[PDB]
Length: 216
Image 1 (tube, rainbow, N blue to C red):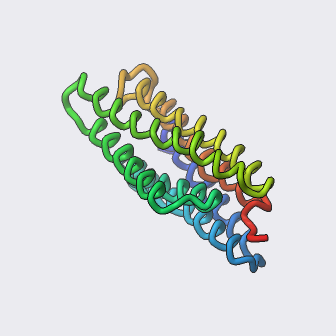
Image 2 (image 1 turned 135 degrees about the vertical axis):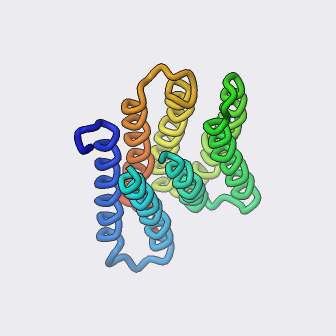
Image 3 (image 1 turned 60 degrees about the vertical axis):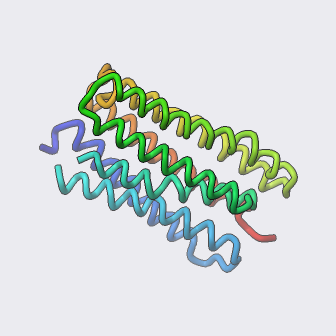
């Protein structure tokens, strides 16, 4: 059982998600700044949720748990970016709403037992993702550029990372078993695991290493 690729990617994801959470926790201790504290709480919670979900997949070894974790973590990563650029509640609510639709229709697309329609839900989900990325790349950038150099600089990096990593999911889904079934399950599980760690631990490392989180 431990020799199967699928199990190995799940075990690795659990380990990396666990180590990241602990590292962020260590880094977070001995930080008094009120604003910085908020970023550490959100950013530490993200990989902690994923750790639990990846652990749950191992214990049950199914992937219905990945969507549940995407459902919880995607909104939190958006809040992180929203806090960084001091976005207004209205735009935040719109982002989370679009995000809920994105995750929700994605799951519906994977549950449908009638082909052709798989792509209909994928198109709706991808459209929702595109609205979010549009808001992040064109809307948040303007607000960030009118702010402190450190904030503007870290946001652009997090922005570029988010747009590229998130855009990869629809692609992997389409070539994977939920879509056209071109790439085997173990390769897809690997692609998602790599994307998940990069989008959470990777993203969190860049954010938490920056002075942009401090109130100043």
